[PDB]
Structure formats: structure tokens, C-alpha cells
Length: 210
Ligand SMILES: [Mg+2]
Image (cartoon, rainbow, N blue to C red):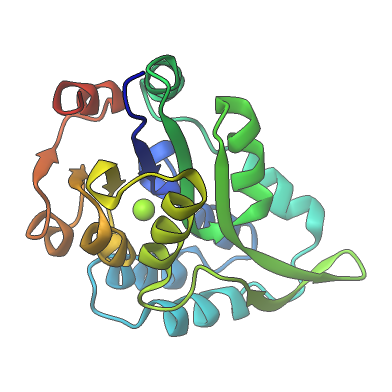
């Protein structure tokens, strides 16, 4: 009869080792420029949505096959599946909320056995990226809105939620969460975290969760 907890994870650099957008940028020949903007966005120096639309536009015309080649290089962070299975083993609900893309996130949702997955989407036409991106994980308070929505669906009080993030777009998720864990995170998020983990193994979060 114990109560369930809801645990939300950020995708890029948290559940997986890579930054999806930077990997696709490599295939489009704009890795350096995109990497730089990604770093500023995660450090909180830029509005997230404007920074993402700017990086995605540099991907215009990339064939879908090259997008997949970049996605295939994405690997799960050390300890990811074991950690998710242990949380589910306790009866907890687990979700991934990402400013990244369904094309990468959908895969990991099934691979790791997550209950919820929210991400943006790359627009495609004639088998190539158009350079646009649309979705519900763009606005500054988007992740916090999703955390509240999932918690309501599950009947779980916000005090019983845990957010694990690593970038500035995880700040709104931290505002609503009962426990805030910064996983090998940028300074702007570490300032706001309850706990900061710097060892790159997702199982390290289990020590802090009953
Ligand atoms: Mg991240």
C-alpha cells in the first residue's frame, strides 16, 4: 500500500550520453556552431525556444537517413536501465521530458521501459528536414507544466515527485518538484538543486530516493 512517486528525467546528457541536436548537426555540417548555441542554451544564456529554432534551422534539407545515422550514435548513460527498473520495481512512475526530439526519445522510452515521454518534433518533407521544429517542450515553463500534468493524471502530490536534470530548461521542472537532483549539470541548475551528482552513473540518484 505505499505511495507511488513520480520521477522525471531530462533526456540529452542525462538519460543518454549525447546531445541529440549536436549529433544531427554533425551530419548537417554545422556541428561547431550548433554545439556553441546548445552550450549557451543549457547554461541559461539564451531563451530556449529561440535557441532551438535557431539550431534546427541550420539543419534544413538534411536527408532523413543522415538524421538516423546521428540518432544511432546515441547511447544510454551508465546505469540508466538498472536505475529505471529499480524505480519501477518500487511501484514508481517514470517519465522522460525533453526539449529534444521524438525521433530519438520515442526509442529510449521503449528501450528503457518508461511510462511517459514528452519531446518536440522535427518537421520533415520529401524525406528531408525542413528546418522547422514544433512541440510542447519549448516554452520556459514547459517542463514544469508537463510535470504537473503527469502528477495530476497519476494522482501523485507534487511533494512526491523527483526531477533529475542537467540544463537550464530543467529549471521549470525543478520549481514544481519535491526533490531536485542535478546530474553532472550546468552551474545555473546546480544552484537550484537539492542534490548535485557529478559521477556519471544514473544509479547514484537511488541513494537519495526512498
Ligand atoms: Mg539535458
